Image 1 (cartoon, rainbow, N blue to C red):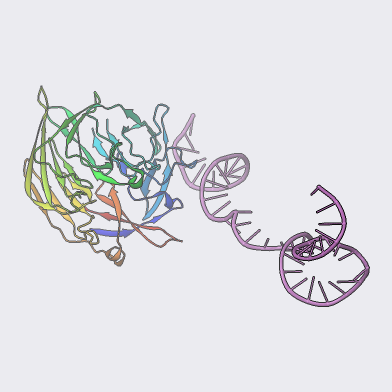
Image 2 (image 1 turned 120 degrees about the vertical axis):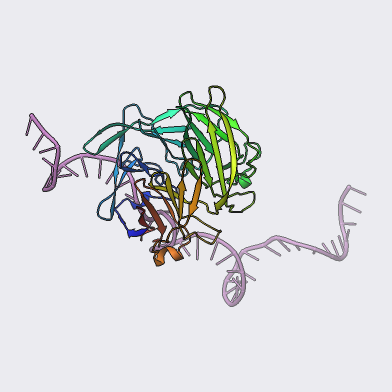
Length: 342
DNA sequence: CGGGTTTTTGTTAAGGGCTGTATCACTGTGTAAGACAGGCCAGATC
C-alpha cells in the first residue's frame, strides 16, 4: 500500500528484467543476473537485503557437491516443503532454452553465511519441451506431493525452425504435466477445457487445487479474463485431474503474486492492454472450495510509474514486493522501488 | 623469275607544347571495464 525509494549499490547493472528472488527463512536471495557470472561471484546467487532503504548485493558460494546452474531469465520458481525451491526452464545468456530442472536448498548456515546445495534432477517420460514464462506449483493430496506445470512459450520445432525467423516464438500446448519429484517422472494430461496456449499467467496453489489467472495468447493477441480450477487427486492408482472454469476473472499478464496473510493473496502490477498498464491492485480471498477476487484502494503512485512504459518485479516473500522501472542511459538505467502490503 | 616505276615509311642534324607519372610528407580506421593482491578496521572470540 506504501511505496518507497530504494538505492542500489555499485553492481546495479547485474539486475535485468526477469530475475527471480528466492526467500529462505526470512532471507531474500537474488538470482538471474545479466550476462555470465564474473569473478566477483562465480555462482551468480546474491544476498538480496535492504537496510534503511538501501540495497547491497552480497555474493554467495555453493557446497562441494552442487551444480553451477546457468543464469536464467524466465524460470518457473516454486516453493516446496526440508524447505527448498524448484527451477525449470528459462533463457540462458546464449538465448538457449534449458530443458533441465533444478532444486536449490541450504546446506550450512552460520553468521549470516549461507552455503547452497544445487542438485540437478533427471526427468523422464512425458517431459516438457524447453519453455519460458510458464508456472509450476505443488499440490498435497493424501499425504503426497506433485508438481503441476502448465503454459509457457518456446521456439518453433526443429523441423519448422528457419534461420530467417530464428527468433520466432509460439505458445505451447495447453497440456497439463504432473511431475513426481521422487522418481523424476512426468505425465501428460490433455483436458477438454483448455484450447488456448497461455503464457505470463498467475498461479495460486492450495492443498489440492491450483488457480490460473490471466496471461496472454499469441494465437489471438488477447488478454482473456479467465479463472480456472485444477483439482488434482492422488489415489492409490493413477492421478485423476479435472478442470473447471469460473466466472469473475482478471485480464492481466506478467502480474506479481504475493501473500499478506494465510489463505489470501494480493495481485499488483501487470498489463491490461499493449500500451495500457494495470495500475489498480486486486485482493484474492480463499476458503475451502470458494474463491473471491475483490478490489482494494490503489497505492499512491508517483509520476514516474504513471508515465513509464514497462516495469518488472518479483515477490520478496514477507509481504513486500520489489519493483523496478527503467530510466536514462549514458547514468542510471533502472530505478527500483519496494511496495509493502501488510 | 628481274629493270623501271610507283606508293607509303624511316629518319635525327634541333626545338615547342601538351600529357602522364613519380615524389614528398603526412592522414584516418585500431579508444571501457574486469581481475586481483595488498592494506585496513569492525567484530566473534577463548
